[PDB]
Amino acid sequence: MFEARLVQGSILKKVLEALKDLINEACWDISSSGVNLQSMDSSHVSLVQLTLRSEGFDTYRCDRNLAMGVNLTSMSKILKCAGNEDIITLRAEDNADTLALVFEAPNQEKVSDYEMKLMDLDVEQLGIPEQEYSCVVKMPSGEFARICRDLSHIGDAVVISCAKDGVKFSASGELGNGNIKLSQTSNVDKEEEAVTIEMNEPVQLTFALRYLNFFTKATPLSSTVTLSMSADVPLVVEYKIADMGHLKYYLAPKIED
Amino acid sequence: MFEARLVQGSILKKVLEALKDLINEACWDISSSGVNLQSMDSSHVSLVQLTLRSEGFDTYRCDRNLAMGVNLTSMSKILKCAGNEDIITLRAEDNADTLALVFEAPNQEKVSDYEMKLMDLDVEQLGIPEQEYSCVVKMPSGEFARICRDLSHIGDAVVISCAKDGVKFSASGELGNGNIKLSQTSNVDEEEAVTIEMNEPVQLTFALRYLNFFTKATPLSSTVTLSMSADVPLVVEYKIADMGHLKYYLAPKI
Amino acid sequence: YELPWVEKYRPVKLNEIVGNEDTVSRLEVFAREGNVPNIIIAGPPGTGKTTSILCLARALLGPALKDAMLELNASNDRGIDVVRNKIKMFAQQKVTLPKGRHKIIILDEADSMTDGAQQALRRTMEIYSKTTRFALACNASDKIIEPIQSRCAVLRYTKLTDAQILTRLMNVIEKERVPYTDDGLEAIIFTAQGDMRQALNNLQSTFSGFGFINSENVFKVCDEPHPLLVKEMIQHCVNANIDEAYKILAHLWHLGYSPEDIIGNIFRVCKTFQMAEYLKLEFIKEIGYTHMKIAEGVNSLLQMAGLLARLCQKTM
Amino acid sequence: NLPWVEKYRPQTLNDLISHQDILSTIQKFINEDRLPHLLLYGPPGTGKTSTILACAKQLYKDKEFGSMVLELNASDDIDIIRGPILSFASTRTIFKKGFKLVILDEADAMTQDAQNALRRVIEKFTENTRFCLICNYLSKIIPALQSRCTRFRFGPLTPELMVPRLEHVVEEEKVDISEDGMKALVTLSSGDMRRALNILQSTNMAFGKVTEETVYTCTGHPLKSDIANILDWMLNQDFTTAYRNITELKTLKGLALHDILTEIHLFVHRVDFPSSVRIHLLTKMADIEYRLSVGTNEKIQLSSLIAAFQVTRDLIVA
Amino acid sequence: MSLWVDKYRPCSLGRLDYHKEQAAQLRNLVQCGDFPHLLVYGPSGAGKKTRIMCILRELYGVGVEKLRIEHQTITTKIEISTIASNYHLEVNPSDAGNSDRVVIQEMLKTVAQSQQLETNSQRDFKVVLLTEVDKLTKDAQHALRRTMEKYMSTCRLILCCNSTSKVIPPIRSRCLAVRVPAPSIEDICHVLSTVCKKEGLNLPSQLAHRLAEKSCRNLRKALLMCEACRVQQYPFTADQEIPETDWEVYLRETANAIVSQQTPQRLLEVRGRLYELLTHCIPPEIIMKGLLSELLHNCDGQLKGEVAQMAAYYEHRLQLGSKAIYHLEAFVAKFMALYKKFMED
Amino acid sequence: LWVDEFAPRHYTELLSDDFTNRCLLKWLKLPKQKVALLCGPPGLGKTTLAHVIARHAGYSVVEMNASDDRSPEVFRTRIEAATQMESVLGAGGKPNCLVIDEID
Amino acid sequence: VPWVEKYRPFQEEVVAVLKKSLLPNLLFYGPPGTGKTSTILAAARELFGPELFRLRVRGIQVVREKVKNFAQLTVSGPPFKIVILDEADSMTSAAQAALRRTMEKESKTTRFCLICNYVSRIIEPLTSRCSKFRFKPLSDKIQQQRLLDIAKKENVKISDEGIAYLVKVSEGDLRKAITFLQSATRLTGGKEITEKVITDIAGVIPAEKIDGVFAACQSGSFDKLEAVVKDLIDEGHAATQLVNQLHDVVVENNLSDKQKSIITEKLAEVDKCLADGADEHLQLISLCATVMQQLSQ
Ligand SMILES: Nc1ncnc2c1ncn2[C@@H]1O[C@H](COP(=O)(O)OP(=O)(O)OP(=O)(O)O)[C@@H](O)[C@H]1O
Ligand SMILES: Nc1ncnc2c1ncn2[C@@H]1O[C@H](COP(=O)(O)OP(=O)(O)OP(=O)(O)O)[C@@H](O)[C@H]1O
Ligand SMILES: Nc1ncnc2c1ncn2[C@@H]1O[C@H](COP(=O)(O)OP(=O)(O)OP(=O)(O)O)[C@@H](O)[C@H]1O
Ligand SMILES: Nc1ncnc2c1ncn2[C@@H]1O[C@H](COP(=O)(O)OP(=O)(O)O)[C@@H](O)[C@H]1O
Ligand SMILES: [Mg+2]
Ligand SMILES: [Mg+2]
């Protein structure tokens, strides 16, 4: 008899639409400690992990752990039917047969509820290890989306190089060559626009820009995005949710010639 | 080696966007006097004249005049990557195959560089005679753009009637026909002062599809200049602040 | 790690290509003179078309090869729009080259693009021919449209003779000091079927699997209906000894070979079997008809038995 | 319950049978890191896919197995080559190091242009990606494509090396099976383990007992006694009564002319006919079997088979 | 309304001149409800189109005769021409090449949708008429039967073909076969006399017999030939020089040339004649049948069986192959070899 | 190269034994046909035929091919402007000639 | 309304073993009138109860993708849903191979119960991967009584020997005699259904024509064969029907074994040629020439 009441329901819609383009279906590792999602890319190149801590909900009542798996596209589609200021509460039975989505208007009697058909998926825990990264970049989400979408016209691949002074985004393609140099923010009062770069040794990796365009869909979730990267380890893109959790992304670097 | 810099980089993006639809392959005449472009369609329906005076740019350096072919779609895709407040610096060698243009944020710790490839385009431009047009119309660019947009729906052809009291815009189609007349104003505002200089009444018809393309230069200036004669192709000119001018030529209908 | 022998010993210059000597010399002449026209390469796979084209482009463009050469493969998208957008814009792209040099567009597996793509490619080939040249490569020349061949110098390639295969293989052996025997060389040549790539790959796989190269190991790794047994098959068919031919066929079938493999190897043996020319043509026609029946679904052992019977009755 | 074909699918290298040399070679390649691209071909249901899955699971743990092995099937379709396959092969690993792995089940279904695209992709990234191509017919593979990989032929399972595997299932799934039932189960399987398991399960479901007559009825395959009777009728009885007997038997037991014709083919080669008579019979039976494929009337073909045999009687007696 | 073939074509089933029992059966079928799909078949020039037109005349009003040109396109796009009326549509889908299946599906969709638009003054369905169904491809026939099952209630199908050999059993298993035999010699004589008499003329019986036997029981041939011999010379005599089509004469001359000399140069001349024949788009089977028919007139009785078997075998090979001349040339060469062997022995 | 350099300039550069250039000029003067066609074997200089005719008559030249995406709307865009629009030049060069290449 | 669907129905035993599975893929074949679809529908209703409904299934990609959309869906919980795909033999070989692949990767959730006319459907799911079941056709006597009842209730004026002829021309299966009778009574207007009407409806060649063909063959003059074959073709009789009827006649005559063998082999060759679309007239001429050559000795 799962029950989870969320006051700020608009977050869930942004969570789903950030995944529907990359992942079609996923298993929600629902536990009394919170909601967790970890699904891997269809082409097996990338990977996404999601964590929703139980303390962030208005009321969390996961009496027993669930391994619920839904369709991300279908779940997102219903979520557009929910207003940006409507209270959203998820509910599951004593057994995970159907998903009860409850949309409650903040100040009027209009109440909407939906039920979702479920899915059976054979998934396994994937060994995401915690390591220190030789390069950590903390830059505005909008700026990262701008850079990713700009170089997408240049070419399908982007070369990311970092130094102590700043980070350089380089690309090359059929219409020409271009590179964006972003120096570390010398002095800005708030990080929301500051570009914070922490690095140990110089790094240089190439990534497909199609996925990076997919990755940028989570920009509305948080004003700032953190990029973690090191030599011979996949790029790590994490969006810090407000007192709720994080949406961490993982993408293997492309092959150098 | 050529080098130039434009503080108000938004100008380059706007002139570029408005021109890319008419022309996909244009040659740039770099000169000490400034930047000159004049490209002409294969069917010779229309001509576009672009001139950017050297003193308009913040800095300018043309060691010697050189032509270099440029793809307009590539530039439009490149220039969209530049913010409206960015400062744009252009650079090239004597006969380099690549155009080096740099987008600088307003000292906002961000430097964006690009190196566009050039074409094998070497069509040497042909001069256009100057003529004192029978009717000269100055009137707001947005109004003219709206007029072109509305009349395009009714029909593909517009009839332009020039009279001292006012100009008349007419179009006909299967769904019907409509007319728009702009009386000479009484010095309203000043961009709204629709001014008509009429030496002799003149009637001509033009394809509205091209005129719709011409209106995309609207963000450049709130005012537009219209001038025509019976045998002279219509000229539509936008004053690009003080950088130069962008002149549109279009032949009349048979 | 080490590179596959098909790449570790890929020829890097036109001087070390053992293919059709006249065409190789013509390519060298084109490289020297510079102003090479549009060339189309067709022939059996793995005879060196790709290697020849790459070596020609490298010789012509030299250091400019990085940006003066455009290469598209079946792995890339060669659609109707790509030839209209990538190829056209690359042709228009400005590149300064010496007087005898031109921008080279390489389309390997040229037979793979559709009719519309080649029709669009026609004009782009025609217009920008003053500064851009095309180097097409394909296995079947009929697949590329007639106007394209008309405005190109079609260069035929053929299956390499066993002497050229033996020379290249012995060179590789000297490079690798791999032990061998004449029977192993004959077997590797037979498995090659005039294909350098196939021969090198099979030789490398055989050496990896067993080291010393002999017919036994070669046929162990390159498992196939053994050519000798097929030779006694056909010999028995000539002597009208249907029972012995069936015995060999049943042994092969119990070994588990698919009928398609058996019939293909039978025909291959019928290539070089020493036997009357008219009777050989009769056998070839009958094997062709049986292979029709096999390829269209009827692949039972009974079909191979009927083949043996009809071959026996051809000699009466 | 769960069908026994996957309920008892091999899970480790030891579960596989009759391919110990191939498994040893692949194990040696894995241990020495020289693993090349693999081309596995053979009759259906001989454990090729299970073999490669066992090797991969040996090399890769399940935690990283999903992120380092891209299993795909060709019949699910050129966009596969340029899409997921290219994307997977164009990047290195996520967590572990070393070469990735792509398994392409039913590789023979791809078109020739798709095979060329796959060949180009394979040659481009041979250093860090290995391809396992699984197909039934080697001849369906482009000669250029098969020149990049080592070919392994998985032959049909010989009885005595596949009988013990069935015995384990019988001990597990409690079904009484006779000696002749086991022999017929082997014979109809014809080296196909999946066929053997499916026939065993269908027979158990149908009657709960496995015996030669039971399995032959369940699969519809003609019995050896029936084939001997048909051969005796054609060789001895006159045309009218032979036709009547054969038609009656066929309609009674629902026999198919293809299986009938194959079995008389085997008997013809088993019996001692004169050489010319055998040649004539083989030519005829091949012609009839060709005629069945296009979809002709079965009665006329059966009578034609009888005709082919009935002619020889005078020839054989003399 | 000028040519005798169309002028004297009966309008209704009741005024037919032969197979009147079949006309009565068809009248009973159309009179009772639940009209099924029809598979009309028979030799060309027997009256299949006439019978189907009379069936429509009984099924609907006389307005069915007011045919209209219709042009429709299909997706892939292919544009075809069709003939329809205000109760039915007629189309030969085989002319659309291998894209016949999609045009059949689209035409049936359109007819099914249009029939619901108050096209129910007399019957609750439209008639979709297909000519030369035998030329359709197997997948096209599968789509045809599937759609026929799909839209049985809203539309009905009538199929016309010269033979049922190339029609899939699934279609034949769900359509009502209507065999239309070629009329007998006497029936052709009466209809020729009836046309001759109603026109105000006089046809002697012997001339009618000569026409009937020469027409090979093809009524259209008989009517054309009768009108031609009339305009040539009205006062018909027993020895009237009845004309015949040029290609028949050319085929006969080709066979005579084959018989005359069995040499490779003559073989090449015959090949040129065969090119001339195929050029005029006469089907290869027609050429083979005519060539065999004229050849048998010259062969000895003991040789005719071998020639007939060879002709059948080579025609079958031609059906399997694609290059018609290859197999026709082979048959001609084989016949010349055998005839040379037998005449010279 | 050479072909452009020695391409015909006026009517005096035409070759003998050609019936095309000597009879196209009569139709293309201002007897009321709308469209043209090309037939016969190649090698007759049909590509330069209309160009030389326009050069002799002073008319303008427009030529296209399948190098651009040949959508029907794109066809309208490419042909309506070339047909129904005058020239931005002196009155002499205003008449135009149009050529379509690779119809299939 | 057709009378076939009106009255379409031995093998209720196979339902019990299906319910006992609490599952190899099912394959049901035999003559089409054996009630296979009704049998599987009844088995599904009994196994899953009234409250559980199921899909039934002309393209191959669409069919297989629809199979994914259904089988991909979860179930309330019985565990396995069985897919029908009747008319399996009508599917092309490539379609059947794609359907075979679709059978895999969905066996973990759904199963299949194919319905076809036996050997016409391709091998690799026919061998293994399927539990085959044969549906015996009803006995000729029972079919005769059933058609008698149908004639009585539908007041069709047909005699008992007419019923025997009708069930004869519908060799080995039902629902062909039923539709033949319906067509016959609608063509005749219900006044009387004679045996010649049934002969015309079923396409059977009258035996008198076969007797004339045999007499012409026995005559020994090729002109008579040419004339009789021309007449037979002019009657519009399909060459396949002539081959079948003459085959049935020949196989039970008093001809020599060699003669019967040669004639039947020629019949098989002619049938194969007609299957490929060869000309009917030429094939019939060749067959009759062979029959002459055998009968004139
Ligand atoms: N003449 C040759 N001499 C030596 N090695 C050769 C020769 N031809 C081919 N090879 C070897 O075969 C390899 C494959 O050749 P290449 O890629 O040029 O084939 P290709 O003939 O263009 O065929 P395809 O288009 O089918 O791939 C070469 O890298 C080289 O190792
Ligand atoms: N060598 C074997 N030992 C034990 N079981 C086997 C063996 N080969 C096949 N099987 C059984 O047959 C089933 C099917 O095997 P599998 O599909 O892996 O074979 P395959 O030869 O790769 O065939 P295909 O190409 O048809 O998939 C297995 O799940 C297993 O139950
Ligand atoms: N009458 C002529 N006078 C001068 N040069 C001519 C004449 N006719 C043809 N040529 C020359 O012959 C060549 C043919 O050029 P063009 O492209 O016009 O030929 P085309 O016959 O239209 O083309 P294609 O043969 O490809 O169909 C050119 O070099 C052209 O200058
Ligand atoms: N009963 C009849 N009375 C008069 N003329 C007829 C009769 N039946 C057929 N015909 C003529 O014979 C011709 C046969 O044409 P058609 O119907 O196309 O033959 P088929 O359809 O059998 O090939 C028709 O044009 C028609 O004029
Ligand atoms: Mg190559
Ligand atoms: Mg397998």
Image: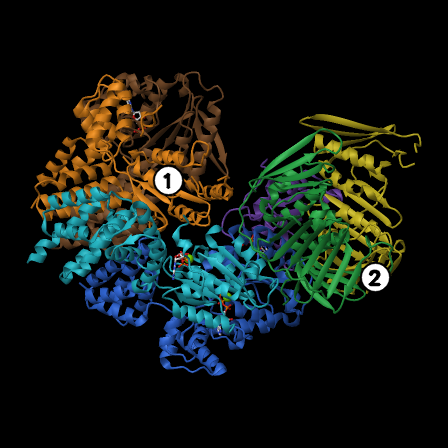
Chain colours: A green, B yellow, C blue, D cyan, E brown, F purple, G orange
Q: Is residue B115 above or below residue F102?
A: below
Q: Are marks 2 and 1 on the same chain?
A: no
Image quadrant in which the N terminus of chain E is located: top left
Tell me the residue at 59%/35% (across/down): F32
Q: What is the secondary structure assignment of the residue under circle 2? A: strand
**Chain for disc number 2:** B
**Looking at the image, can residue G154 be seen?**
yes
Instruction: Please state which of residues E295 and D100 is positioned toward the viewer in this rendering.
Output: D100
**Crowding near the residue tagged with mark 1, few <14, some 14–19, many ≥20 C-alpha atoms within 10 Å:** some
Q: Which residue is mark 2?
A: B3
Question: In the image, G100: left or right of A1?
Answer: left
**Ligand 3, image quadrant it occupies:** bottom right
Q: Is residue C249 above or below residue G66?
A: below
Question: In the image, B145: left or right of F66?
Answer: right
Q: Is residue C152 above or below residue E84?
A: below
Q: Amino acid at mark 1?
A: Lys
**Residue G159 placement (x, y as % from top left):** 18, 21
Q: Amino acid at mark 2?
A: Glu
**Looking at the image, can residue F2 be seen?**
no
Instruction: Please state which of residues E341 and A51 is positioned toward the viewer in this rendering.
Output: A51
Image quadrant in which the C terminus of chain E is located: bottom left
**Chain for disc number 1:** G
Question: In the image, A18: left or right of D151?
Answer: right
**Residue D214 placement (x, y as % from top left):** 25, 49
Closest to the camera, between mark 2 and mark 1, is 1
Q: Which residue is mark 1?
A: G19
Instruction: Please state which of residues G28 and C218 is positioned toward the viewer in this rendering.
Output: G28
**Residue C82 placement (x, y as % from top left):** 60, 53
